[PDB]
Length: 91
Ligand SMILES: [Cl-]
Ligand SMILES: [Cl-]
Ligand SMILES: [Cl-]
Ligand SMILES: [Cl-]
Image (tube, rainbow, N blue to C red; front, side, top):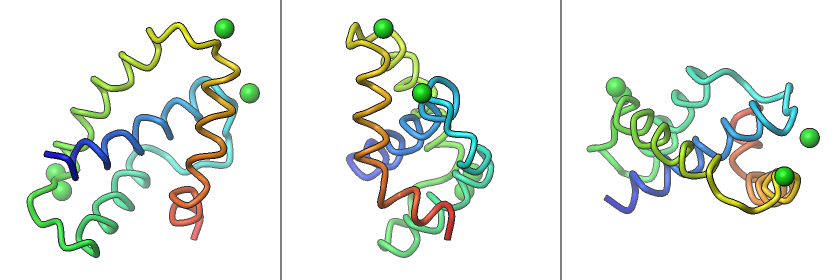
């Protein structure tokens, strides 16, 4: 599912920021998943569950850690790209 792929990618990138890019300001995993579930339900996505998003996000995260891009560039790319989602997270 592309909606699941999308949501899971946003959640895994946010985990990457928290774990490897010092983003102490971001909410916890439960909060992030709640917000992803809220967002999905607003977008009319009824099939997506927090467990589906969480499981796929785990798998994406592993792929992200293994990617040979320098870690600091990963951080810079995600910090720029997640600005909208982080606004929903902190709202
Ligand atoms: Cl950092
Ligand atoms: Cl759910
Ligand atoms: Cl769930
Ligand atoms: Cl590196």
